[PDB]
Length: 82
Ligand code: HEM
Image (tube, rainbow, N blue to C red; front, top):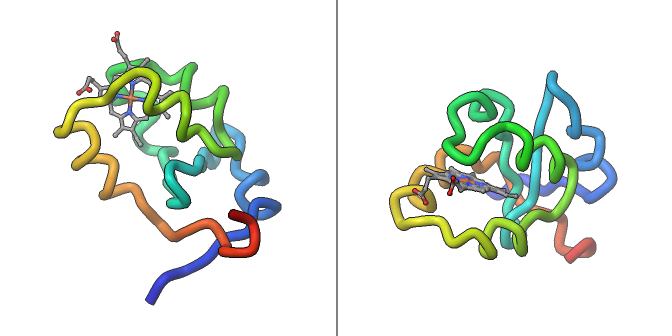
């Protein structure tokens, strides 16, 4: 089933040991992706622990990038925090 994470819990994952971010209500664990991301590690680290949906869409990722992003989904933002 779907696992929910509250905004409070997501905010704790804003470091090198654990980098999580929110995109369109979905939670992504990008910890192991930081060094492979074509756009660099900095833009990810800076948005860690929060909603980066706007910044993500503002750069205009390709279909391949979006398809790949799905493999990093670990749950969704708790409904009451949306
Ligand atoms: C959800 C995980 C994400 C994946 C899997 C991902 C994947 C990629 C890939 C494959 C590219 C290469 C171009 C393309 O195929 O569109 C790219 C470029 C880029 N990404 Fe991401 N990205 C993710 C999240 C983000 C986020 C959250 C930001 C910003 C807050 C970001 C900023 C960038 C930037 C700036 C580039 C541009 C590189 C350039 O033009 O030199 N990405 N990303």
